[PDB]
Image (cartoon, coloured by chain):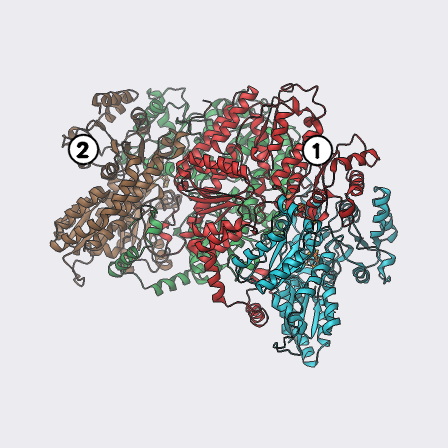
Chain colours: A cyan, B brown, C green, D red
Amino acid sequence: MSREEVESLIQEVLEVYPEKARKDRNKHLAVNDPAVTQSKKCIISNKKSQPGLMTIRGCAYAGSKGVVWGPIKDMIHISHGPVGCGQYSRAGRRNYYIGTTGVNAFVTMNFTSDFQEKDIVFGGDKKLAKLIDEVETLFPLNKGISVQSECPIGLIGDDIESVSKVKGAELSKTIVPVRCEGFRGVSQSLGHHIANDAVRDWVLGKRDEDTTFASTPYDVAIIGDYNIGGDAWSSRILLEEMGLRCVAQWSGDGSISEIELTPKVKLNLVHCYRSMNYISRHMEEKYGIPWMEYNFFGPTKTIESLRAIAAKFDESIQKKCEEVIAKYKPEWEAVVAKYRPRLEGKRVMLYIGGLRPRHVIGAYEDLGMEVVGTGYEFAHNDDYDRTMKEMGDSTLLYDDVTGYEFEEFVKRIKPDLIGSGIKEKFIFQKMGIPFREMHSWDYSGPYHGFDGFAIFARDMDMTLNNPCWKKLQAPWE
Amino acid sequence: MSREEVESLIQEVLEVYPEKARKDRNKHLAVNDPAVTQSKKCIISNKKSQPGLMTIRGCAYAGSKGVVWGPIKDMIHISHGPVGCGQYSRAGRRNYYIGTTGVNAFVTMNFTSDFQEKDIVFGGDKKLAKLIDEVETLFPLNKGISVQSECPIGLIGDDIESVSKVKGAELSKTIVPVRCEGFRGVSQSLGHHIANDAVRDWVLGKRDEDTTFASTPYDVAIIGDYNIGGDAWSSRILLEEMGLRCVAQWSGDGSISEIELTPKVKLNLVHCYRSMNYISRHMEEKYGIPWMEYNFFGPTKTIESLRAIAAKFDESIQKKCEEVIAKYKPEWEAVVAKYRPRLEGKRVMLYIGGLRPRHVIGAYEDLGMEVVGTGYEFAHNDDYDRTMKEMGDSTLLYDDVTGYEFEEFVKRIKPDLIGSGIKEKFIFQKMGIPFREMHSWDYSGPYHGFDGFAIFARDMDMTLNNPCWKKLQAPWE
Amino acid sequence: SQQVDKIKASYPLFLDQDYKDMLAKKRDGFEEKYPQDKIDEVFQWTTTKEYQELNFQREALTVNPAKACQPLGAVLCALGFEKTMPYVHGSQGCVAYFRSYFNRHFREPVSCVSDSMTEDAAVFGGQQNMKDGLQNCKATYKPDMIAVSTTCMAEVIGDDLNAFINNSKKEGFIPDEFPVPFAHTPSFVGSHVTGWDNMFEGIARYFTLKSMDDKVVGSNKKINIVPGFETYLGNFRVIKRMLSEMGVGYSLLSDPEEVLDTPADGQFRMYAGGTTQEEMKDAPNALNTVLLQPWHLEKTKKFVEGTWKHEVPKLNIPMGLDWTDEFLMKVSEISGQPIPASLTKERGRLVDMMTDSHTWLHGKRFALWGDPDFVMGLVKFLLELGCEPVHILCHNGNKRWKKAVDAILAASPYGKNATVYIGKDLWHLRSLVFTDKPDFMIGNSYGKFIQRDTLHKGKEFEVPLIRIGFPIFDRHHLHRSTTLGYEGAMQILTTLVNSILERLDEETRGMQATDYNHDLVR
Amino acid sequence: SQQVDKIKASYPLFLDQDYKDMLAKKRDGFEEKYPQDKIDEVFQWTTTKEYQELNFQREALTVNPAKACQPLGAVLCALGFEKTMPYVHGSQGCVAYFRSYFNRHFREPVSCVSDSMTEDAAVFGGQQNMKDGLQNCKATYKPDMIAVSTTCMAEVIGDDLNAFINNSKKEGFIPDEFPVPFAHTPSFVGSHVTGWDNMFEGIARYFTLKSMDDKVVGSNKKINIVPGFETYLGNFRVIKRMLSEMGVGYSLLSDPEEVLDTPADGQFRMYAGGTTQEEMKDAPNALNTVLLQPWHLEKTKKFVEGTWKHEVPKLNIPMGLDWTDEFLMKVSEISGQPIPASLTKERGRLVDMMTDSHTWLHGKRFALWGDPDFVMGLVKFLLELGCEPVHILCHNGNKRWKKAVDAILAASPYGKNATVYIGKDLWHLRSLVFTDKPDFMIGNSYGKFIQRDTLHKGKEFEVPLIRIGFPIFDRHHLHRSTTLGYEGAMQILTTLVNSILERLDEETRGMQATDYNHDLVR
Ligand code: ICS
Ligand code: CLF
Ligand code: CLF
Ligand SMILES: [Fe+3]
Ligand SMILES: [Fe+3]
């Protein structure tokens, strides 16, 4: 709104920084223009954070262990290093799964080597081999081990690749070494890249020579959906109602066998482009599997995605797609009729990770809500290429925003709702602004698909229109 | 010992009273002499309380509704009068039963007529008939209605007998009017008498002309056991292991059919003489059924009672009795071996209603404990005749003791443990004396039989030897 | 049989095979029990809407009431004065029941006496009973005051307390200067809160009615606080703390929190704390009188406004956020003291808790019961949290109270599904929770049986109980809690949200069935 | 499918038939899952004593630990000083994880920064990182103090904090007078409590080591209180309240209760309260220093005794009756202030609660885990109540602490069946609760999964969890509780007895099966 005001606000916020930090941060804040197609001319992304400025970014270990490898349920994932990292990331992400924990599923469990001073001084490869033996003894029904590195592993001269090779040859088990040390990269995105490379190098090609899996022309894989609150399940059902067959989903509620069967499918359906574009491009190049993006956020995006997917197949699939759309139309129409009057005209600001800042806009507009600012923690420039056409004119765009910047922007813009993570929720709640968690769904969800849209609308209404937001000022003040 | 000291203590305590109260209370405190067989020459009981002296006694409604009629599970008992009495007595007594509450059992529920001013002014007989109709409508599986009177019913001139007769003829149901108004009598004892008279007049003789019940020479009834904490059950099993057949059980876990079948048994086994001697004497006079007292408190009394019961039957019953005693000997021997070293030499003071102050001495002596004082709230002079021979020389005997008297006697005697009710527990707990509830078993039990003796010993040890009794004095005091 | 290493109490010893066979033999042989299928059919019928229609047609039968009688409240009021003996003129069984009730709720000694009226007094009256009882009570327990109430027995014969106490004083049974306030508390009128109101009005009249000539309003720069029937010690504590933090002079009349919270240090204290006779005599000199629970202090309000000439403010119970704010601003206006920053920070902290827990609180459905002021404060707080009160029950409420509660409900969008019931008992409430299932119940211990019944229908039909109210018999030390002010609101909010979260945890503990939603972080 | 009137979240929407069929098809078609009988066999094997023997032979594998790393405790210590910014020299992922952890436990904003060291500093060092970070942090957030700790990355490369901060000051990045205390907190040594100790020692050294010439012991007539790692605001509050009631001058060093309990009133406060620099500079002038949690304040004790010349008393954590009494008498002896009557009455009231609940508490078996001082205080209190600690676990404890705990256990007859485990994790504890079943567990939220496992074996094998400790993620506002003093003992006692009573209520709710023991009065 009123572009010159937004640029003035940007300058006023930047006035406080030292010259180096101000000059750097000036390249990461922008005023959106929907006509612009290339983001390199307006915003700069995927760079190192300025020291001492309260960034929100994580590390490559979080991007690899917590995002990509952790949701794999039948594998045991071992945090190689000191005790803190696996403890802070244990069950913090709501990647839902079905299994018997401790027997054949291990998602919420924390396996670690628990480095001491002696391990730092004299290495930890012998400890790693002994620990792998112990894992094999105590958890027989596991189907593969991954070793996720923390910072000291890369800092000291540890060679986890040789240990993994020897122990895998000895036990006839898949052991995947992931060099996802924290100091690599600038954020979790290099963790995504490293985890995808490990998947390609150690898992994806097991059944290249195997041809015992019967294949159908309607075989698809779900890539980049991590089943937050059941999200992937809420997507999968729709695809099965269309008549497709979902051979695998990466990686929420995912098994290693599904990953190894993925090269046998006819189409890849990529949900999170940011974290899985590497593996999808590799399979297109190697196995010739086409991949396409889809968006199941809100009825409009869901219907458009379903039609786009069905067009990739024959006419029976399109007929089933129309049947599914007709079946689900009354339910989301009822949701819209109930909740749009309570949410029309509200203004939303978002600060999320790599995919969701632009994916959720359509669902918000399906309830009459306008997104006035958005930003990414770690996403690349192609993500901003998509976002710039996704958003409106004179809206605010921020990359790797600092706490001070986000607080000042929110003070000036005064949105009705903010969607961000755990580290901004209470900051903006004490400020008197409704806040929804857009990583964990505030322990609600799923939000994907038609069944998720109802939950999304109910949550928006329950937080935006709660009475507690009208009680922050004492009557005597 | 020290009889002269005990008498001097009695005089010192009585010194505070006014002349009338002192003269009255002097007849209710005594120093026991085991050689004395007539209590009327020693102590006086069953008299009205002195006003304003904080007695512990209840009323006739408590003795009838709460003690005798309430445990009958398949009957609905209606508190005729204002709302308070049935509310304070609802589920306060732990008479255990098996049934589906609200459908075919109604023990823990409170049915009342809830008198208002209009009911007081214009009577409540029409309200009673309407209420009986509503009871029949809403609780079809009930097997009889009893109407327990409160004070205003007797004071305003209501004719509940006519209503009961008319509605019983109309509905073909047994309706028992009980004139258990509070102001009659001096305690719950007249409630016992009135409830027994109602049982005799309205229930006991229903199957006098009915001879379809097959009878065996080993038919007994349990009379006066109210299944506190399951006590009656813990007795019944032993009798069934002896080979007897328990036809009725008065009145804990009792049904109206058992009461009506009682006149068909070969022997009555009276536990509480005080509350059931009336009905047992009536059945001896009318049906010729002999009755005998028994005591299942502690292994010694239990074994003696079992042998005394078995002597009333043939030799097969005696052989079964010997088998039962042999079977249960190791268990109570183990209990004694475990708990007597922790409880030997301790001194106990008791104040319970009408049977338990004398029945529990044997169980205490089975753990090496000496009872130095005992007393009754409402028991008669024959109860003291039975009591005096069971207690030691120069021990204290008190009838309808006041709070001030009880406190001063405990202060002078300093017992290791006191067993009394809810209204003295916290009084003696703040004094630093261990206290066990001897009405409700402190929500523990059962205490009857061999299975109950283990619970009794564990409870005595856990309360007497608790560390909290050594912490009442601050270290800086 | 018992193993000495692991002894079993009634549960689970009676679940052994021998006891089970004994019980089955007893039932099959001598109980003439209905067939189990018939019992199941009747239970299912009692869970239906036709049964509810029959149940609400009741006119003469009360099943499981949610109230007590007046002399219980009179005793509780009398306990709040310094070295005062509660004395109930009537039958001793009433006093035994009152003492047992209060002992089980408070887990403390409760002192009360009776004159033990019998059938002789039922014919001739209880004048001699009162003379002897007053003399004996004063001689034995040495109180500074004897507060006399009545049982229904003495009410029905029409015993004149004033004349009987006057004759006791005239003939030398007790000194003429000894204070003996009295109140008629008929148990067939009202409930226990009515008895509290009657006893307080009697004591205030006794100490102030005849000596009003030298009274000037506002002379002692204090505010009188009348709490009413209260069974949470934290409520007295929080009122006193909040008034002290404002620097406001106050006089709490009928304060029993010291005598219900005596320490265990090797001695028994029959009396502890309480309102002094000097405070009660000086009460007309206060700036004003504030009644914390105005819906059962009507007689007290009439006396204070008519005699003391105090302009009693129209205040709701200080429960929740808005009503606590209104109480604080009214006290500030009366006394001229500004509201301190500590209370502002406490209010902000409560608001922060509300913001933190609003997501788990929103849309939840509650059935609830209790006393009128407590019930309406609870409804107000639940509306403030975005919760849905659905079945609001108050056995001792009236029509004006119901109209006020309906006005509260109509002002909020969350009160559209709420129904208020006056004069209904807990069997009605059982029918309501079966036919229109809420998420939770709020009430005293008598609700536990209702939960049991719901569990009999099926696990998906269980309505868990949250114990707020009087009496609570199956939990320990809950009477130390607070329900008033910001602190009480925080305690209630914590209890509610954590009850919701334990229910969710229990419902998602099934391995490989529902434990996909067994989240570490909630 | 969704009904707009009753929308379902993940639970129980995924229990619908269509979702169940989808999941069954997915598992049967593409997951290559083990047969359910094989899974059941392996689970039963993991519940056995042979599995426990294999499990305790572990030497290199840690499964579900019960501790964190040092910089988390360093951040918590730094948060307790006035207008102080916690600054972790190292990698930014660590700071993200620390902030998320504390946000989830406290439900409050937590402020911390890092210098964001990357692969470049892995060979050059983080000198430029520290210069730029100190300048940027001071310019942007305006702290009065920056407290520097380290991550394992900078510890492994061997970054010299002292030299780097000195070079930052010398070259003008920050003023020379600006306070920048620092501490090396290697995450491969000790745990979070060790980091708290290191950070406190660094701050105290920075403010006192070079200016000890004009210090006289006892000049300010105060007692220094060092709390250590603490995540209950009620503990700070109760210590301050008890010291104020005695009339004892005190200085609480590292007090974060204000900054972790800010109000919601429309503004964001990055800083609130905390120990001032004047208090820390004046600390050597106190009469003495009292350490509340002495088993992770060894470095602090060495510094205070060696440098400040304070004769630090040998005191246990003031948890439970005896240790609270000892703490109060030691404080009274040090300051010369008598113990007031209010604290005597509070102690008596706690003793009264103990007397009331001893029957339900006696003989109960508890597994428990946590931090060393917290754990030994819990064991002492449980012994005082007549309860039986059986499995005592502390992942970050040592051999001397275990010897002290064994000495405590041997002094009590209720410690006969207790075993102390040091260096064991929660998978060991799962084995222990399976093989020697206790009645209850006491611990943080990570215990919930153990309960789930026990429920999988059978309802008679479930071990319910009582949440006392850090962190608690699945309940709201439990961090406001108290575990210290008589008030903390009362809260713990109430929670324990009521947990026992809810378990008993749940076990006796079966109609006509076990509800013969569903008592109204307990
Ligand atoms: S993987 Fe990525 S930060 Fe694509 S690291 Fe992050 S479960 Fe975010 S915006 Mo948390 S690139 Fe997924 C994400 Fe998006 S953990 Fe989740 S919500 S769609
Ligand atoms: S950036 Fe990432 S989270 Fe940080 S360490 Fe590095 S991989 Fe890990 Fe675990 S132990 Fe603690 S938190 Fe660190 S300092 Fe040593
Ligand atoms: S001695 Fe006994 S308990 Fe007393 S009344 Fe009489 S029958 Fe009953 Fe119920 S209602 Fe209250 S408590 Fe009484 S005063 Fe009117
Ligand atoms: Fe008590
Ligand atoms: Fe908060």
Quadrant of the image containing the C terminus of chain A: top right
Q: Could you tell me residue C13's position as x and y percent?
A: 33, 51
Q: Do labels 2 and 1 share a chain?
A: no
Neighbour tally class for label 1: few under 14, some 14-19, many 20 plus, Cα within 10 Å: many
Q: Report the side of A256 relative to C182 (left or right).
A: right
Front-most of residues C91 and B443 = B443
Q: Could you tell me residue A57's position as x and y percent?
A: 73, 51
Can the viewer see residue D396?
yes
What amino acid does circle 2 point to? Met
* Residue B437 sits in quarter: top left
Q: Establish if D69 lies above or below A322.
A: above
Q: In what quadrant does ligand 5 lie?
A: top right
What amino acid does circle 1 point to? Glu
In front: label 2 or label 1: 1
Residue under label 2: B388
| SS assignment at label 2 | helix
Quadrant of the image containing the N terminus of chain A: bottom right
**Alpha carbon distance from label 2 to label 1:** 77 Å
Q: Could you tell me residue B309's position as x and y percent?
A: 16, 49
Residue name at image x 62 percent, y 78 percent: A214
